Image: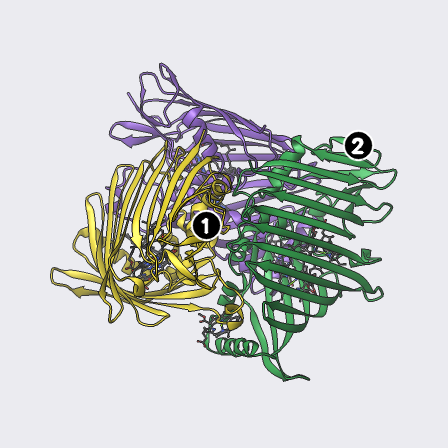
Chain colours: A green, B purple, C yellow
Amino acid sequence: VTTAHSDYEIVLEGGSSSWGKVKARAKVNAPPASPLLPADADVKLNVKPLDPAKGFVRISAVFESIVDSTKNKLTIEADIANETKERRISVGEGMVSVGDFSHTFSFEGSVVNLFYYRSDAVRRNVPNPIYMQGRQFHDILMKVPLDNNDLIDTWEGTVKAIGSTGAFNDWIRDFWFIGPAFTALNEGGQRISRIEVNGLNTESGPKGPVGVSRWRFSHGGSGMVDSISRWAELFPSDKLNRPAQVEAGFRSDSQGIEVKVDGEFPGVSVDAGGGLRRILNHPLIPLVHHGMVGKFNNFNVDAQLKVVLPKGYKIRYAAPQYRSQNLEEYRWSGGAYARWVEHVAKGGVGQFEILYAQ
Amino acid sequence: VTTAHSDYEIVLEGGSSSWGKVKARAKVNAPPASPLLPADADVKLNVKPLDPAKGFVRISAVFESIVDSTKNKLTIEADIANETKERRISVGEGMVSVGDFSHTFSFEGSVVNLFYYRSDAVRRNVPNPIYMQGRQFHDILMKVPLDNNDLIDTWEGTVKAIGSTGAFNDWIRDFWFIGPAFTALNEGGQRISRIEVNGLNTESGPKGPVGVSRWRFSHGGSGMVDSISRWAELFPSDKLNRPAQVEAGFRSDSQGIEVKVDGEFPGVSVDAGGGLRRILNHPLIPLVHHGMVGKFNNFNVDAQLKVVLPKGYKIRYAAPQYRSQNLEEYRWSGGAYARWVEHVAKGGVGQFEILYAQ
Amino acid sequence: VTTAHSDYEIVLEGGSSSWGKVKARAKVNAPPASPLLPADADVKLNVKPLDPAKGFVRISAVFESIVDSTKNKLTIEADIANETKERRISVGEGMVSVGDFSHTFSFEGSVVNLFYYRSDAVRRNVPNPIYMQGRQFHDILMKVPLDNNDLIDTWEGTVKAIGSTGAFNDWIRDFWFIGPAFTALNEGGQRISRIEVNGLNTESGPKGPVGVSRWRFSHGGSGMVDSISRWAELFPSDKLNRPAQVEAGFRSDSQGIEVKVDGEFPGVSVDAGGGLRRILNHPLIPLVHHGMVGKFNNFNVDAQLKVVLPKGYKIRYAAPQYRSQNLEEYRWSGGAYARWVEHVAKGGVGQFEILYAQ
Ligand code: BCL
Ligand code: BCL
Ligand code: BCL
Ligand code: BCL
Ligand code: BCL
Ligand code: BCL
């Protein structure tokens, strides 16, 4: 018998605060859909206020994994700020390593997020809008020291390809969205444009030649792509009054999958209007993308959610309904909640709303 | 335990008549995949002979819904006629309303449906062909009175966009196929071309300015798109000797879905050749599209179908086989029928054929 | 209760040999997702060494089916050889028949398979790479005697279309990937280019006019398309020291599906390095494509695998683990193996690795 066991905990700050602590654990005795096993990964994300006056934060990410004995790592650290409601700017650096190979990089880039329409007729009549169609434009300048022969080979190969292959800006997407990543684009109503290569040259860096590229692309979303529809919400820099962090990891092999998440960050709750608040709307891409793997083994659900509201707050509406309550702490399990967990784990996006207030 | 309960009833006219009464009810205690709940809708479609000499019918549609408290409505009424086997013409009017906002519209449009091949070698050798690849071309002239400020804003915004944005005819499809509608295109082997904007201007209508647009698009189908493969069959104007109608609705929320259908129309049965008739072949798009939502909760099937043949007719072949019979009335439930209901509810298109005769 | 019963047997040659005998049987009491039933098919593939000095083999394929009473057949026989590691050449002939219609054909064609990158940094650090992004270019010259009126009609229709329709090279793909074949492309991360028509003319053949076309297309793969990622491996001509063959067939209708496979060919095992061997990595397209039909009825798994190693060899690693062993013969059933069978039958590609050695 295949059984998914999971526990989730949300502990909320009150007042005007959107912050929450989020913890999760899950295990299921079914294999992942990776054609290489075992596959283990640990991820740590950190972000701190940097310059509140200019709205800059400093964010870092560390990814480490082991896949069929191969050890991988990627880190990236960047300073990011909104310039306007639509244009965001970044500058950063990082590295990637795989077994005995590694390389570094630095970059700067701007992203401009544009909705296809704006209408007060929609805004005033839909209290909790979900879909927002739009397109996001990246402009990136990246640099990689060419300080081993593999880097040199790839740089020269790519220079040669760009020079000789008229369809490079098109076919590069076949390379980029490796394996089933390609398939996931259409699944989420996401489109990636042909790229533009605006600049390609070698620089004389302090330790040697540096490969420098300037390039652009856009990606379109029909409304489910959270990176576009919830662009401002997903970067709550104006709510980051202290450092935030999240650590997560999984272990997986032919026998099953185990996962753990432990984080604290702003944006967990939202002003719902009318003096109510809600847990933020569930982003759609995680459910749709995970939906591509959640349907391969039947499973029973053994799931519990615990939500701790701030002192003095009460739930006004929850659907699925909670099972029990002890002051500010509410618990869901079994019944309609278990059924909703099955639904979203298989790719469904049916709404689970929690509205609360003092 | 998740259980889908459903009942279907088909009552057929005899002789040369293709007409039937179709009733259905279903309920299932699982949530819909809507990221806004509750979601309730009622739909009424009507069509009557208008000018049998020119083949015009007058069709009307009313859609009403409530989604997370927002009240929606759209109506459309049109006169439609075949000009040729491939070209159909229409003229009509309607309105849309959402909360405190509303607008009207009128239009005329032609649609030309073209198959990619015609071959007697296929026709004479395949007795019940299903797939037909082809492409359908729309040419539309629509008008909307710009009689509130939101209409004015959207009209001017769109005029501005068409003027400034070279990729408008491309990216408009991201806006148009909102949310998971985008994803459904590829699922059904359906392609939407870039649009052509042939005309855009303001008219001085009786009550004020009117926004007028003339535009075109084609959509391609690899064979499953019923709008293309069964183009003539889906508009049985030559069989409409009296008014036809269908009413349907659903209620849904975090706890489940309930639905009801009650209609009467031509085209329910078909001449199968050899003096046999069949219930029409199941259209594929409904099953494929619904397949995108039917896989998120395991369910047991409690389904019954009742088919009442005209007096004196008998079933010659049915697969899945029926369970019971009382004169002209045949009933299916359990066993292989329940298994077929599960199959098609999850997106399968395995054939369930009923052939009958006197 | 829906139950899938299946048995698989692999019997391996030893030494440096990659050959194996592969047998399979499966049955399941659920309907196929074919909108025409019954659907029965038998396939026979044969290949023999032809000219070991030039690397030519002679391969033949016979497909026969019956679909809703219509009898179909297609045969193809060809000589195929690698010219280089990337370029393969072929010349051959065949026929197609459907009911009272038939036609023949002959052809020659080259295919060039190109990976998007080559990197020693990947090669030396990933011991068993799976994804390889790339693009494959076909150049085909085919001839069909126009020796009945239907052939003449289609030839003239196509000549007319190519002449009049600017989007022919684009829309031809709607015709080509009939029905759900269209949808399967994106599912497997596969792209088909617009075609190029380089030549179209009529020849005066011995018995009459012959329609001759010269045309090209490429197809891209993001890494799962085995035709691209495992290009050399899939044509083990250098391992074909004697004839190989496989016969397979299925019978299906509204009640269920039964299938049988019986074959012997090189390429069943692979040198894994370190003096180990493995069963070849599971190709991804079969699992992904079948995944599009494997999710419509819940089923229980009654599956057994038997692997017979060459004398004196032992399994070093298997995950899922085997259940029993008798000398060189190992058996899997139930437990984690049954769970893996469910997973891959529904479209999962989680790795099942068997490594063995003396
Ligand atoms: C990922 C989905 C979208 C996308 C959506 C966005 C969004 C949204 C943003 C960017 C931004 C950036 N993108 Mg982009 N971007 C995509 C694909 C790309 C690709 C590529 C080759 O595929 C590249 C090179 C880039 C490059 C870049 C940079 C120019 C820029 C800064 C990145 C950074 O510092 O990351 C650092 C990396 C990480 C922090 C790793 C973790 C990333 C995941 C997604 C974050 C999960 C947050 C978690 C749920 C809660 C975190 C709480 C913690 C306490 C922080 N994008 C795809 C198409 N991109 C930012 C920008 O505008 O800069 C100007 C920005 O806000
Ligand atoms: C470059 C990337 C972008 C960015 C892209 C996104 C995207 C895209 C999304 C978010 C979302 C969220 N982000 Mg943000 N985000 C950025 C910076 C920040 C900052 C900040 C001050 O810098 C903060 C505090 C946040 C905070 C938040 C939350 C409001 C929200 C997640 C809520 C939740 O409950 O998660 C619960 C958390 C978990 C269940 C697990 C989180 C742990 C794992 C490790 C996080 C990463 C998972 C992902 C698969 C990894 C992909 C990595 C790439 C391949 C490189 N982001 C940068 C600028 N963020 C999500 C959301 O809901 O938006 C509305 C969302 O979809
Ligand atoms: C919907 C799937 C296909 C499509 C397939 C068809 C087909 C097929 C036809 C049209 C026709 C029309 N289409 Mg078109 N069309 C599509 C997308 C569009 C879009 C758009 C922005 O997406 C627009 C503006 C149009 C516009 C139009 C008009 C020019 C024209 C008349 C519409 C009408 O009166 O509807 C009135 C609206 C309704 C009746 C609502 C109900 C619609 C559903 C689909 C009908 C279900 C029938 C039910 C199962 C049985 C009904 C029995 C009742 C007793 C009647 N189409 C997509 C791509 N279109 C018609 C034509 O050729 O006119 C010249 C026609 O026959
Ligand atoms: C503008 C739209 C087009 C059109 C488009 C289609 C399409 C597309 C299809 C049909 C199909 C059918 N149509 Mg027609 N149809 C038109 C006009 C008509 C007229 C007429 C004389 O005007 C008649 C009598 C019919 C009759 C019929 C039947 C032969 C057949 C449904 C059989 C059945 O058992 O349904 C059983 C009915 C039900 C199970 C439920 C019906 C109730 C619901 C409310 C109907 C609409 C559902 C749909 C999801 C709503 C989408 C609305 C849009 C978003 C606006 N149509 C107009 C001209 N029609 C279907 C078929 O099988 O074709 C071969 C089909 O796929
Ligand atoms: C099928 C998936 C890919 C593809 C991948 C490949 C690969 C890979 C190769 C070709 C090759 C060829 N392709 Mg191609 N090809 C595709 C689509 C096409 C289409 C089309 C209209 O769709 C056409 C006309 C062609 C035409 C051709 C010829 C030019 C050439 C020889 C074919 C042959 O003899 O087949 C004979 C037909 C059969 C043997 C039928 C069986 C085919 C199945 C796929 C084989 C299963 C093997 C089985 C698992 C184990 C067999 C063991 C037996 C003992 C042999 N391809 C799609 C896009 N094509 C070959 C080449 O390069 O020639 C120069 C080659 O190696
Ligand atoms: C024109 C077609 C190409 C070609 C295309 C492919 C493709 C594509 C693939 C293979 C794969 C394999 N091929 Mg090869 N292959 C060709 C010629 C050969 C020759 C030869 C010396 O000529 C040999 C010995 C082989 C041998 C092999 C094996 C190494 C491997 C299957 C292993 C296994 O366990 O299958 C177990 C076998 C079965 C489970 C059942 C096989 C029985 C059925 C009848 C085979 C065909 C099924 C398929 C759905 C039919 C599609 C037909 C088309 C619509 C026309 N191929 C020709 C040149 N071959 C597969 C692989 O794993 O590659 C890494 C794979 O994906």
Residue under the image location 41 percent in, 27 percent down:
B336
Pick the front one: C354 or A141: C354
Left or right, residue A357 beside residue C218: right
Q: Position of residue A210 (x, y in %)?
A: 62, 80
Left or right, residue A334 beside residue A16: left
Label 1 chain ID: C
Residue under the image location 71 percent in, 44 percent down:
A128
Query: Which mark, residue C288?
Result: 1
Q: In the picture, residue C161 is in which quadrant?
A: bottom left
Q: Position of residue B290 (x, y in %)?
A: 51, 39
Q: Evaluate whether residue A281 shows in this view.
A: no
Where C125 sits versus B180, above or below?
Answer: below
Q: Secondary structure at mark 1?
A: helix
Please give the residue where the numbered disc 2 appears in the rendered image: A325
- Most distant residue in the top direction: B326
- Number of numbered callouts drawn: 2
Q: Label 2: how many residues lie within 10 Å, few (<14), some (14-19) or many (20+)? A: some
